[PDB]
Image (cartoon, rainbow over all chains, first blue to last red):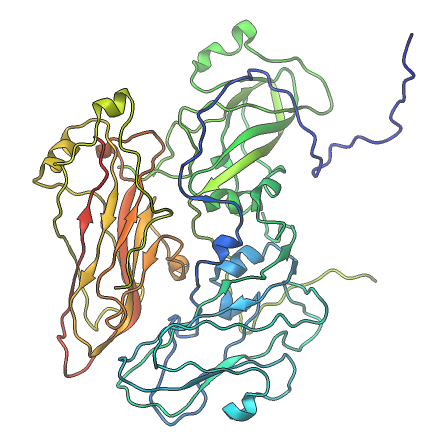
Length: 221
Length: 161
Length: 182
């Protein structure tokens, strides 16, 4: 009374992604319940919200030179996922192990001069390919721009919408084309009030929308 | 959001260099840039079940922690015999302590507790390890690849012909 | 003020338990404050100037007596940091409760703020306030052979001074073991 055998013609590979399980040997041992032990996280995302970052410049010093002079342009830095501006960075550090992604990078700002001093500053987006960096905050305003002064506040956060070609993009970059991927988005300012010295800080963080698809080892393990 | 739940990322294998007729079973013999150890290091306190896969010859034998190593070959404590070509098992957990960790600052050699164990046979060629249901606690710093040249980065990309 | 900032939770604690707790009950009179020197901080120090302080030191207190009593215990930790200056300066220093300290390295400097933490600047803050709940690989601990907790502060923003400030500035803190069960 044999049951009809159905011998497997050519399947059953010892391949990685399989979810099959196994059998214990010296098994059947309990353990204490590990509820209530603080420090629990489940997603690099949420913990990739509550923390800012610290950018970098050729001065090797995070903070930015901030001169109380008649200059009109502050400084220009790129923003990307693989760029010298954002290497030592928690978002990217998680990222470099990914090829697919969709999410807005976020920012922060911290001030140095005494509260008394008056000031103005103007954030300014730029698309990847305008072929010309704007040379005045009004004609720079065309892309995206905003304001927040010394008045009533010191912290501030701002973002840049996840523009692309299609609803995804490559994390790493190429050696087959030339055009920058995002632009040179940086900030403008109006007449400085007074300072013997100042300083600006900026960061990054994931907010609502940071997304990834995965995985592959890039490294030379 | 349908990733960063480690329960999906930490269910694969990774290589181990060292081998011996008697060999040790612990995570800290990982590689410190293989993606497994990327997150696997990134926290403070973690915990899982265990699964392993071994290609070998002879008679693979294992024992939980806290034993006399001089008391293994004899008396054939739990074990099964030999069979080619593949072999897959899963070990349960033998805590002397209610959670694992990475490093323990005391007056920098690794402690003697955290020990998934040790295997022994007559010919041991290939090892494979696999985490289970793990959880992570008190995350820690992390780095990316270092930057040397000027602009952003450059990297070759595969394309058809 | 900016207020209080807890570590990973804020809640009344368990206080009474089994044979070990019934033997290591919540004694109260082993609790008291004291201050400790942190560092000098003038316009000289460039960025990255790290400094550390292991915990806990000795103390001529009953707490100090039992932490020498050379046996199993447990504890909590409330810290409150501050310093004195004047409104004619600028910059920011970074403060952080430290789980599982290790000797750091250059590149990772830009990372210091996974931990619970606060900022330091003359305008915004004048008094830190943080607390960390217990933990440990065992149910309890015995110090002399380990230290699970230290406390760190390091340079974050360069300091500035004009002709109307004290060209030397000092910084103090507040050590406070709490919720103790011996």
